[PDB]
Image: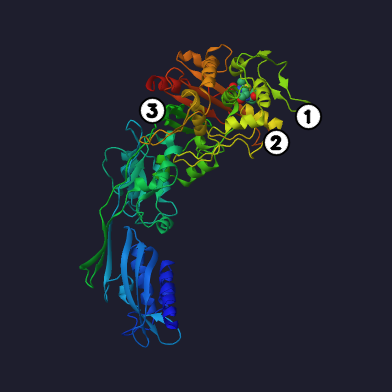
Amino acid sequence: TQAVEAGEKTVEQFVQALNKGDYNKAAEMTSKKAANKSALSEKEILDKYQNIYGAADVKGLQISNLKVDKKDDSTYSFSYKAKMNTSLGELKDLSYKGTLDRNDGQTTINWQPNLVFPEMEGNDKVSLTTQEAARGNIIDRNGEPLATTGKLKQLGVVPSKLGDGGEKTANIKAIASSFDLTEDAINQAISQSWVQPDYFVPLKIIDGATPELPAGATIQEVDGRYYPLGEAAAQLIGYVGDITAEDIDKNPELSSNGKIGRSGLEMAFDKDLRGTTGGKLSITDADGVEKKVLIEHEVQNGKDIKLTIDAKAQKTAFDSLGGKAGSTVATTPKTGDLLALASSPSYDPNKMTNGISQEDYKAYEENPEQPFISRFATGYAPGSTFKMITAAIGLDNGTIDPNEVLTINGLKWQKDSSWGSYQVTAVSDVSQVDLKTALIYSDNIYTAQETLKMGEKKFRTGLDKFIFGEDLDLPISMNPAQISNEDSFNSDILLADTGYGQGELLINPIQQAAMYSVFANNGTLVYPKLIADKETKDKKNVIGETAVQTIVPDLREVVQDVNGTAHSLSALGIPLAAKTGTAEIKEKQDVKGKENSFLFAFNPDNQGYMMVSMLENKEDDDSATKRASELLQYLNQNYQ
Ligand SMILES: *C(=O)[C@@H](NC(=O)Cc1ccccc1)[C@@H]1N[C@@H](C(=O)O)C(C)(C)S1
């Protein structure tokens, strides 16, 4: 019995050393190379475990149902079920047999070929044939392609088959003249540090007919991932990259020759898009004739992914940002379909996945405007657009009378002398300010006074009915919106700032589109949705229908009133309700404060579309409002 317990520890450590990928430590727990003992030496056990388990990408060996007893004076038998992960799938239900040995005080494993796979005998080999799975496509709500896979002919020259003296110069000139490439660039590539005589130095990417090939040039067809919208959806869609040996160690079910999603939806839906590797893992005899099969799946290509995105709206939303720092979110607010998720500046995903120079990659990473950031998922202070939420809360809890006219003297205001030098500031000197006026001119003082009058308790009570702190059900990495840093403002100043969208508020554009959706659904919050087939989910009674019917007519006046901050959008001649905002930020360099321009706009007649556009670190006279004319026209015509 005391010996049977030591054997269950030996089988445990032997399996553990195999599981931990240390095939040498497991080899030293075996007996000597002899009959009725170990079949091979230790160096041959290492090389057999390394060759076979390495070829099958064997990872995560775990056993169960261990049964160890006694067979003779020095012989102990052991059995167990086992399972392991391979590049083909899960290899479960493995009945392992063996015998232990107690020669001195230690117990060793009489190693046999049946301890690599159950039915191996003598000089049996292992064979693995695999078929790569085609990565699925990504498409928009109307079927247009967003990310597809295909073949790409790649021109390239062989330095050895190019020439010696003069003939190499002649072949370079013929390759240059027959492929439209400068002669100074062909020599710059074939002379790089990595190049060797008999290598394949790629040049151009043939996108049409293959022309006449001079001496030295040769086309090598390769697989590529194409992105039709390109940079206009690079943050959302992401890009794929060549699978590395580290990736295979983490998930053996990958193809060491395929691509893996690195960011965005390409990485988010990597499992669904990449498919499953097909093939067969068999045990052959000593000559290569197949005996027993261990795994066999057929190649199953990846699934396609259909998004709520509109390819036209996505490209228009991105183009309207003119390459400046910003982002635009367009939805159908009654269902939550995300029509566009643009971020700017961006990077070339085609260039990123189909070969990018190391200089260009550093440009993308050293760019201060940071093109790799998904700005529709970055938290910001919403600014003056947030007054709609504060107003709706003040109307619901009976704090704001729409017709009551506050008197506001001057452009500065503070509650009392305890505020020191801090004062809420108004841009327009309007003395008689009611709710409709405060939304048209965007008056901070009215909002600050009504927030302080409301109280912190009643303010948060209305705020907590929204999606602050919630994690949206979206395949986009994202932080939840927050009201402040802590559960209490503990400051009348901070309570006031939060009233008109400043303070410690952090709400990303997508979360803003979800929160502002209440004004298109009579106070019901409709959650955003990116997968076209998902079910619409909502959250009712977030604000009162009374507040919606009061505020939306005022938001029409933000566009229609001649002093409205969005009056430039009345040139469209379409039903629009809007609210602009400009948030000031002092979290970069103290040399100068930076401003973020915002625009919220939806159709108040049919509620077909909703838009939340942003400009980060805006230039002067530049706003989100002056750029939104084109996207609004498209959404108004195509989403009624
Ligand atoms: C809301 O965001 C308000 N903004 C400020 O009080 C800060 C600010 C920023 C730049 C210049 C002056 C003041 C108001 N809303 C914006 C807007 O709707 O664009 C105004 C510029 C009207 S102030």
Residue 464 position in % (x across, y down): 57, 34
| 526 over 121 or under it: above or below | above
Q: How many marks?
A: 3
Which of the numbered marks, if any, corresponds to residue 490?
A: 2
Query: CA–CA distance between discs 1 and 2?
Result: 14 Å
Q: Nearer the viewer, residue 262 or 632?
A: 632
Q: Earlier in the sequence, mark 2 or mark 3?
A: 3
| 96 over 148 or under it: above or below | below
The reply, left or right, for residue 452 in relation to residue 69 is right
Residue 137 position in % (x across, y down): 33, 40
Residue at disc 3, secondary structure: helix
- Label 1: which residue? 418
- Contact between marks 1 and 3 (CB within 8 A): the answer is no
Q: For ligand 1, which image quadrant applies? A: top right
Query: CA–CA distance between discs 2 and 3?
Result: 47 Å
Could you tell me the amino acid type at mark 2? Asn
Label 1: few (<14), some (14–19) or many (≥20) C-alpha neighbours in 10 Å: few
Could you tell me the amino acid type at mark 3? Lys
Q: Earlier in the sequence, mark 1 or mark 2?
A: 1
- Label 3: which residue? 312
